[PDB]
Length: 303
Image (cartoon, rainbow, N blue to C red; front, side, top):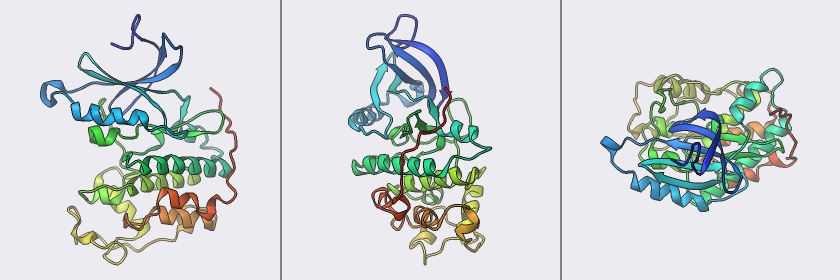
């Protein structure tokens, strides 16, 4: 393959298990750059060759932005699939866990949200959705940058219920229109996910930690109120909507994300509107008053 003792890439160490395959830190023997090498194994004896997926993912190599983890190459070889990606030293899930006692400082939360919205605004302007954003695919470096990894993969492969190691794929960041079975996903699904991640950075706890599809939905309903045709036209006609859903009242965001100020609560509320058409866009969010004083702090990382 591309990784091994004498291949194009030398393995440095395993850095994690992704949704689709194992991820290695690797060194390119010719250019000397260190990369993240993602090895997706294909179900060849029942799915056949994934030509459509290779076509779609290869288009992502031109989708370059400072807040998008660069897709350096797509390698289809020996009937397996490898993604060669820019390497960054830590993900936001590990950084949040390591910051559990103190919290991430608010100026760094604001800087990260600002940069993530820039990356979304870029991808969405090129008509590319992520669809499975979560802290694990937000990567950080020591200088203060944060970048989005794995754009385009969910669309090419689908989002499975379990990973390749049979771990549960988290539902915590999934937008309500996905949970309710909408046939069309818009860029709004990523804004929802980012809003959930924003809240988690602020409070140091997941906003909606559902452990099943219905628990995820009902956790959303208990906080935001059970949706109706008033706030979400068409919601009662969605494929998985049931009129027997309990009717919870909406909670004040002051209880949901203390100690976020009014600007941040206003932005978060716009990122979590039920109606995807009403949900704020990434570009509109960048102009929100919450970012009037945004700065670029350096985080305390030890590698």
